[PDB]
Structures are given as C-alpha cells and as structure tokens.
Image (spheres, rainbow, N blue to C red):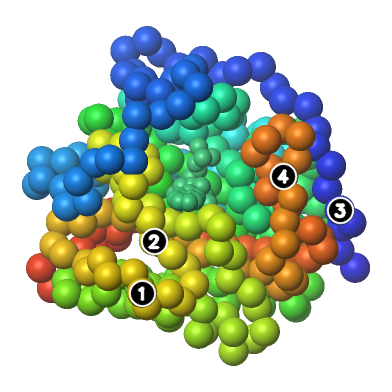
Amino acid sequence: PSRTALSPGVLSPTRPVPNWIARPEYVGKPAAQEGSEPWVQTPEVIEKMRVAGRIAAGALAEAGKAVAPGVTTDELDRIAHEYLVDNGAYPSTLGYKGFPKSCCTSLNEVICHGIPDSTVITDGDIVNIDVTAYIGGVHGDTNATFPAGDVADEHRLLVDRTREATMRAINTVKPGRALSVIGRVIESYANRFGYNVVRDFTGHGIGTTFHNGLVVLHYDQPAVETIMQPGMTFTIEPMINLGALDYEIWDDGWTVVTKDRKWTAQFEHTLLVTDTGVEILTCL
Ligand SMILES: CO[C@@H](C(=O)NC1Cc2ccccc2C1)[C@H](O)[C@@H](O)[C@H](O)/C=C/C(C)(C)C
Ligand code: NI
Ligand code: NI
C-alpha cells in the first residue's frame, strides 16, 4: 500500500541569498517582466545558458540524491537552495509572483508547483523536484520525479514511462520540425497505457526570461504553426496523469493537485535547437 492524500504543511523561514548574487527583476513584485521576448537566442545568451543549465542540473541531482523516506520536502529545498547560492546563482522560483521557496516539490497527486514544507516523504512516494537557476542574466530550468524506497508497480511504471516520453520528445528536436511534434510524441506514447497528458500546464521558451511567451504543448495540437529553428531554447516538461485531468489548486494559490487524487509524474529539461538536432542544456 501507498500513502493517502496530502495536506499542506508549514513553511520554514525565507532562505537568504548573498547580495552579490543578482536577482531576476521580478523578485518580490506581483508580476514578472516576461512573455514578449525573441525565441531564438544569441550565441552569448546560449553560452551563459549552458552555465545556468549545468548549475540547475547539479542542484536537482543533489536534492534528488536526498530523496528517501523520512526526509522532508523542506530539507530538499535547503539542499537545492544552498547548491544554487554556493554556485553564485539565484533560485529563480524564490520570489516569482510571491512563490516562497527555491524549488517546487510535488509528491504523488501534486501535478506541479508544490511548495517545500514540513511534509515528510514516506516509502512508496514519487517526488518531483523542479529547480531553476538564474545566473549570467539567464535561466536554466529542469525537474525529475524520484522514487522514495519501494514504489508500487503502477506508480513505478508511470514514472519510468513519463521519463521515456520526455526522452522521446527531446529526441524529436531538430531544426525545421514543427514544435507540435513534441506533444504528438508525448501524447501518443502516454495514450498507449491509458494515461492522460496534462493540458493547462506546459513547457516554455526560456532565456533572459523564465517564461518567454513561447508555449510548448505536451498534447497533440498540430494547428500550432511554430517550427524549431537553430538557437531556439525551450523546456519540455510533460506532466502525465494516471487518473483524470481535472485538478484543484490549494489555498496557497500554487499547489496543483489531481481532483481524483491519482498520482502524476513529470520530468523537464531546457533544450537548445542546434544546426543538426538538440543539445540538453540542463545536463551534468
Ligand atoms: C509546469 O511548471 C511550469 C509552468 O508553470 N509552465 C507554464 C504553465 C503555462 C500555462 C500557459 C502558458 C505557458 C505556461 C508555462 C514551470 O515552467 C516550471 O517548470 C518551473 O520550474 C516553475 C515555475 C514557478 C513555480 C515559479 C511558476
Ligand atoms: Ni521547471
Ligand atoms: Ni519550466
């Protein structure tokens, strides 16, 4: 047997960032200045995004190594926060439209945007950790779902198939392909198992802004005309549900849970379209 439905816990104090680490412009403001930027980045931006991606990937790996029964989602946050700040990076989630921590921790039925808190991880849980780094004036965004102890076969299979769906989507990325192939591949694959692909939350262009206005759908919609072009940078971050798509948002305004409380899994990379294919920027 697995855990029953989650409830929100209490937050730890806001974690400090040394002043020499530049903040993204949106910290503490009600909105963010993003959504109207070009989608193909300059070479100088791309090189800085390889640095930001690798530091985010390090933070996600360190916190992922800590996922185990008995560890709280707040403890994960502490590890991601400390890794980012000790690398001179600002945690892009911290202060984004009031979000109060340095990564998102989404267990079980939480589709996305769970807030690290006093929740204790237990055996059987699946734990998504999503960390973004801001450094060099650019962002790098990556996430993965980690099993805690021995996870039930249907939950294990959902995690592993969601990882596969993400890899197959990444492997489609090539200049000249329609962006819509990403969702086509993910949804076709997911539907083989009777899973449902979340529609209202998507991937996104990323560069000097966190969500740059480019939207990357994870379901099939070939009416989107956008093509992949060298220099384009975006995330692929499918959330795939065992149950129905209907969801609710907790009173914190952030935590998104499945209404039927069936579990859901996600993985994410920041990608660069190169002249021949793809380069994963959030790579160790
Ligand atoms: C799933 O989550 C992604 C997400 O909300 N996409 C948006 C959902 C959406 C809906 C319509 C149009 C664009 C987009 C991009 C998001 O980009 C995460 O990967 C990121 O790490 C977290 C950001 C905070 C918690 C600070 C918000
Ligand atoms: Ni993310
Ligand atoms: Ni993202």
Q: Residue furthest front?
A: 223
4 or 2: tag closer to the N-terminus? 2
Q: Is mark 1 in CB contact (under 8 Å) with mark 3? A: no
For disc 3, the marked residue is 5
For disc 2, the marked residue is 216
Q: Is mark 2 in CB contact (under 8 Å) with mark 1? A: no
Query: In percent of the image, x 72 and y 62: which residue is there?
Result: 246
Q: CA distance from mark 1 to mark 4?
A: 29 Å
Q: Is mark 3 in CB contact (under 8 Å) with mark 4? A: no
Residue 271 position within the rendered picture, expressed as x and y whole percent measured from the top left: 30, 58
Callout 3 amino acid: Ala
Residue 140 in view, yes or no: no
Callout 1 amino acid: Ala
1 or 4: tag closer to the N-terminus? 1
Callout 4 amino acid: Ile
Who is closer to the viewer here, 167 or 264? 264
Q: CA distance from mark 4 to mark 2?
A: 22 Å
